[PDB]
Image (tube, rainbow over all chains, first blue to last red):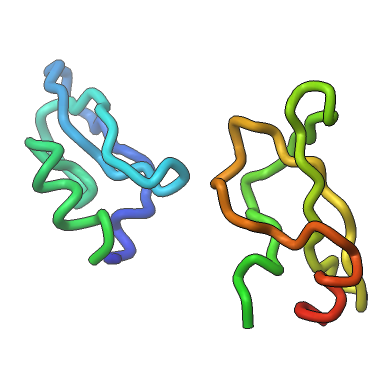
Length: 58
Length: 60
């Protein structure tokens, strides 16, 4: 799987309260986190399915 | 080489058999193996080496 999938979730410097999905490598599946609205990193998905397709076993 | 020889890096706490712990043996990086009592919530369901002999013969 891509290396960016192993990075911690990044809320960022903005103040929005948007729920996004990130792949948690310790658990082996995608979980939710709060995203601030700007400067997203790559481990940040709008749907769990897209997150698993990208990071589940790629 | 079997990945089961390597203790998962995130496992820190051990659990006694009276609380569901299961004994496994992993390589120790010093020519041998050491026992580790795996907590139910950390266990992957894999069939880890269950004796010192099996770990020593497969991992060292």
